[PDB]
Image (cartoon, rainbow over all chains, first blue to last red; front, side, top):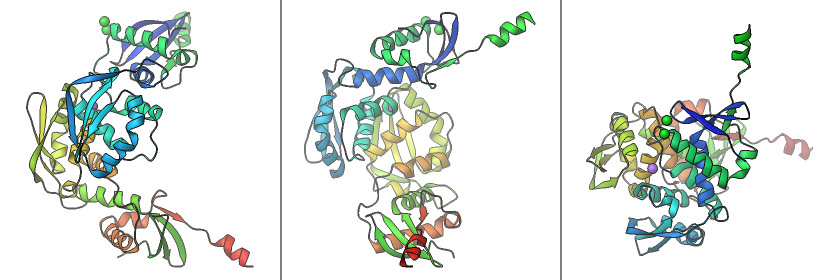
Length: 182
Length: 182
Ligand SMILES: [Cl-]
Ligand SMILES: [Cl-]
Ligand code: NA
């Protein structure tokens, strides 16, 4: 299905939508998040490690290093590969959705998150990366909102069928209609 | 002076069983630690000074990160975190005493990620975020460590002792046991 037709951008990051006479307000940041999670999750989209131009070498504490080692397998399932020596880790590849992020901030952030876990699972790591570590977004445009919803419709069919309250809300016309008649 | 009571024993590697005027309680040492550090980092709740690193930490930042840092510069300086910025990078020149022995190559990027998502910047709010992201103190707490921590918390956070939140301290009900003995 579909969220409908994008009508206009509301308050820099929402999209006013129309579907069968119904008007809705959708949060683009929330939609972007669901999209990224699906694109990063093995089993919901193609996952292929992408080589870094220049590998990112980082110093890590022993507890971080140890966390990285236990997570190696989960990370590789996400397309995140690295090698490491005594005091460092060097990121050699990341999945496509991450290739254009600022990895000098994202990876150290991922490392901090990983150093706090007891269990490592690609699914939960993808979700975390999708919600917290990714590129913030400035003013949204129509072209961007249109593209986003289309991608979300394609990869997250379920969101369409049952959109949470933080994703899309009903814009009630009854008051205006009544006010026009009355 | 006012206190949480007498430390009786360590429970679950990170909690402390307390006794105060006949009442028994369980206190989360990690939570107590976070309040202590939050206090040590908050201007007005404890002394704050800027200590230079012997090796400035340079980091690449996105326009959005760059911008966020710009807006938070004053609040950060109040916390003793000083930095310089050039086109694409920022260089941390100094950090408060409680952050000297941390993994800044991980913590600063996390702080930057956190700041990039804020709209309002206040030293108090930022210090709270920092205290919650410092690497967990110990792992297996000892009696001496808990006794020392609590004495410090008592002097720097007198209000916690008066109104200990439920995340910090919980009552251990002896009534069932007393009834059972009967
Ligand atoms: Cl537009
Ligand atoms: Cl447009
Ligand atoms: Na970021």
